[PDB]
Each structure stands twice: as C-alpha cells, then as structure tokens.
Length: 99
Length: 99
Ligand SMILES: CCOP(=O)(COc1ccc(C[C@H](NC(=O)O[C@H]2CO[C@H]3OCC[C@H]32)[C@H](O)CN(CC(CC)CC)S(=O)(=O)c2ccc(OC)cc2)cc1)OCC
Image (cartoon, rainbow over all chains, first blue to last red; front, side, top):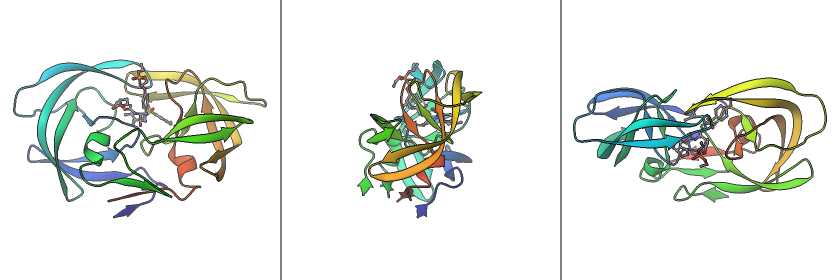
C-alpha cells in the first residue's frame, strides 16, 4: 500500500505466531520490539537511541510478517517504548520513501 | 523522488540560512535538529525514545526546505545525536511509505 504520515504508520505484524502492532520507522537501522518471549537462541546486545543506550536480546533469522509481507531477519527485544520495524526488514518487504 | 532504505535516508535541508544533513524519519512524530542558535522565542520540551528523554527547545513556524520542497512547522533543537525530519514536516512535502 501507499501510507501517508498524518498518523503514525502503525501496522499489524505476526511474529512467533503472535499478532502485534508496530511502527514502520525509517529512522531505525534495526527492528526493536517490546519485551516478549521468542523461541531460539539469543545474544545480548546494546543499541542507542535519542536518550542513550539500552540492553536488548538479539534474535537472528526470525520470521516476521509485516502488513502481509514476509521477512526473515534480525529482531531485537528490549525496553523500547514502542515496537519499531527498522530498515533491516523494511528493505525486505520492498518499502521505499516517495515524495 | 523515490528513496530506498538500504542506507540511512539522509537528505540535505536548509534551515536558519544553513545547510544540514537530516534523516527522513517516519518514526519521529516531530522534527529534532542538532544544537543550533535559532533566533526568536521558544518553549522547553522533553522528547523520549530508546534510552530515555532529552531536553529540547521548541521553535514554532520555522521554514525548512527538504530536497527543494519547502515546509513550515515546529522544530525541536537540542543535543540529539542526529537530525531527524519528523512526520509534522514529512506530510507537508507529500512523503509516503510504499510497498
Ligand atoms: C547513531 C548516532 O548515535 P546513536 O547510535 C543514536 O542515534 C540515533 C537517535 C535517534 C534516531 C531516530 C529514531 N531511531 C532509533 O531509535 O533507532 C534505533 C533502533 O535502531 C537503531 O538505528 C538508529 C538508532 C537505533 C526513531 O526513528 C525516532 N525516535 C522515536 C522512536 C524510537 C524508537 C519511536 C518511539 S526518536 O529519535 O527517539 C524521536 C522521539 C519523539 C519525537 O517527537 C516527539 C521525534 C524523534 C536514529 C539514530 O547513540 C546515541 C547515544
């Protein structure tokens, strides 16, 4: 679809069999989700935002369906204020900015 | 134009008679720019993201040119690690997400 930005670009995602709401975030290099249980091995990592760095759990090669489009990539899980879909997965679904 | 997301969506902006590089950020409600000595009145504000909150100065009705597209709206100035163009201005230049 073509998504305007008068509202937050929120969409439904499916990860680990669970449905969630996430923000399509072109300013995020990576995808960061709120605390949740995901199956598989994970390694701790650090990511920095506008307010500093946080600790996250990094899951590699995770299946995630975004607004009907499938992606398989890295998903970070930690104390983010909102679920954000970052460029690592936006590229996979063919998302571009247009004006 | 069309901007792919393989790399950070950086573009040149013109604000306060200065040229800068800024991120087209669909995840940013508002526009946040690196410290700069803009004239006029301002009101204090706090904005939050990954890592917590930072203090910024809110300037209203500021003209910014983004890839030749003129826009006028609220600009937040503070110790942000990156210049981000938020939805308040992205809407004015007709920017959409497409996949
Ligand atoms: C690289 C230079 O230094 P740093 O590494 C960090 O630099 C940065 C800092 C910020 C950004 C932009 C930020 N992206 C981001 O957080 O992405 C994370 C995940 O993926 C990583 O990629 C880039 C960093 C990692 C979001 O697009 C927008 N944000 C909100 C969003 C938060 C997820 C939704 C709530 S917002 O900025 O907080 C914001 C809040 C309220 C506003 O209006 C009221 C306007 C803006 C990009 C690079 O370290 C500094 C210690």
